Amino acid sequence: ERPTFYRQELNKTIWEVPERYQNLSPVGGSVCAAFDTKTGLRVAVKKLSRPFQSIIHAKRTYRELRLLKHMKHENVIGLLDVFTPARSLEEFNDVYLVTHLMGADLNNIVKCQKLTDDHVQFLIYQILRGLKYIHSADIIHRDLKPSNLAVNEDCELKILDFGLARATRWYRAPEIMLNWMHYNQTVDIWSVGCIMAELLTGRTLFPGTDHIDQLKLILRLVGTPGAELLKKISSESARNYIQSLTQMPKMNFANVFIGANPLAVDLLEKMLVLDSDKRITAAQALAHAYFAQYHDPDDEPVADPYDQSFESRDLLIDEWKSLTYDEVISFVPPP
Ligand SMILES: CONC(=O)c1ccc(C)c(Nc2ncnn3cc(C(=O)N[C@@H](C)c4ccccc4)c(C)c23)c1
Ligand SMILES: CONC(=O)c1ccc(C)c(Nc2ncnn3cc(C(=O)N[C@@H](C)c4ccccc4)c(C)c23)c1
């Protein structure tokens, strides 16, 4: 039951989509907002860029589709449709992904108002709830930032672009930015702390100009690593570099986030720590007293087992293309 497709050029690529999707308008692969005539809702349509023109692209294409088909959670963007104008595998060269269109991203929100404490609580609670789910599937975001957190008029939130990375500087955990010690899923928690601070104050917590300046701003708040944490620094170059910097004492966060809910400050103290072994997890964060009004252990679900064995495979473009085609054809839209 192939739908009828129509073709158009939108500065300056070809978009070939089902007539179902009307009034495409660029918003960003490349992304367009559109009207889904079947449902009456606005959607975001992403055309993957050159999905099968290289092995890296082919594998990324498969990776993204597999992730989107598996993750089903209220705070994680969901796949509404996936299509190709191709009539067969032999003709398969383009892939389009469709999701709900949201109202605004967190960058837009902070630029336009001032958020009350309850508003912050609910947003952060939702981000952590989505992260608990994603992390439970052994997936991490790795590049969580205000631009990939989308909300709709009722403050209902969705996480986008997770599990793809394998401004960012402002929200990046130092252990990955500086490759200075082992890391775990809490790299995403550092990002949440930076985001939460920004929602609370209205300003970027650590707006560094480059990686060196970024570290400088971070250490001004958290304090230079000393003997204790230095014991865990595996990189000799990193140890040498750290010891070359002007030593800074840790700041009491309460003197920084003046006027903030003391519980918000306590939570930030637990997220913004350099030691990856000590940083709070998503699940632990949800249980923090700051979220007492929202927390419900019976409504913070985990993900069904996720098979990502494909990550360890080295296949040809046509092989990844065939696997992707299989997933496109087998797709069943959300009820
Ligand atoms: C696992 O990674 N794959 C993904 O997450 C993944 C995969 C496919 C897709 C189609 C998406 N969705 C989006 N991708 C890129 N930009 N974009 C922006 C919005 C949006 O709603 N903007 C609002 C504020 C807006 C509202 C009005 C106008 C303009 C913008 C959405 C929903 C997206 C994510
Ligand atoms: C990846 O491709 N490059 C390669 O070939 C390759 C291969 C092996 C290694 C060990 C690396 N090194 C890095 N890889 C990824 N991130 N990273 C971040 C930093 C950094 O900021 N160091 C700080 C402490 C610093 C700052 C100033 C001076 C000294 C150290 C470094 C040195 C890296 C790269």
Image (spheres, helix red, strand yellow):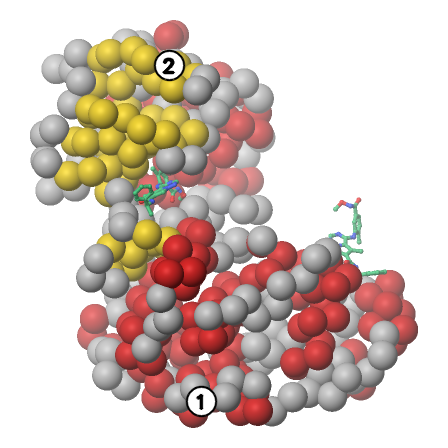
Residue drawn at (12%, 28%) of the image? 37
On the image, numbered disc 1 is attached to which residue? 259
Under circle 1, the secondary element is loop
Asked if the residue at tag 2 contacts the one at tag 1, i.e. Cβ–Cβ closer than 8 Å, the answer is no
* Ligand 1 positioned in quadrant: top left
On the image, numbered disc 2 is attached to which residue? 9
CA neighbours of label 2 inside 10 A, class few (<14), some (14 to 19), many (20+) = few
In the image, is residue 50 above or below residue 267?
Answer: above
Which is nearer the eye, 143 or 258? 258
**Which numbered dot is residue 205?**
none
Amino acid at dot 2: Glu
CA neighbours of label 1 inside 10 A, class few (<14), some (14 to 19), many (20+) = few
User: Which picture quadrant has residue 67?
Assistant: top left
The N terminus appears in which quarter of the rendering? top left
Under circle 2, the secondary element is strand
Residue drawn at (43%, 86%) of the image? 260
Which mark sits nearer the N-terminus, 1 or 2?
2
Residue 141 is left or right of residue 233, and the answer is left
User: Which picture quadrant has residue 213?
Assistant: bottom right
Amino acid at dot 1: Gly
Residue drawn at (31%, 49%) of the image? 77
Please state the horizontal and vertical placement of residue 72, each as a whole percent of the image.
26, 51
